[PDB]
Length: 26
Length: 45
Image 1 (tube, each protein chain N blue to C red):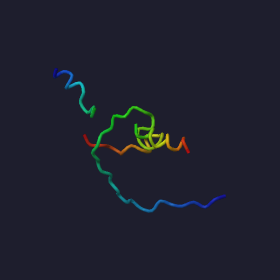
Image 2: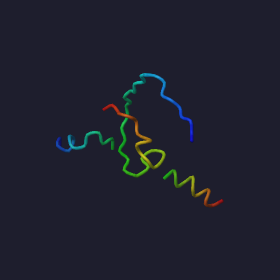
Image 3: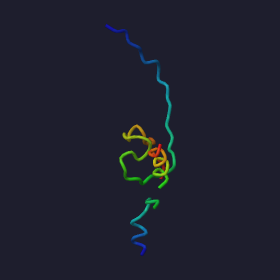
Image 4: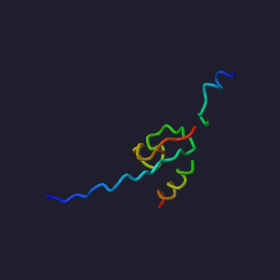
């Protein structure tokens, strides 16, 4: 599968829920 | 009426070519909504 390895060039491929569930508690 | 400023002189500042890349498909894709204010000139490969 070197066609897929060519077809995926430059692709480069819950913490913000944690800091808001504390403030929704407050 | 209003009194206006004037352009000085030919002063040359060139830009430079930075290095990173991004993929992320949401509208903000950075710190805020518009993109041409928050996109790096011309990027290197």
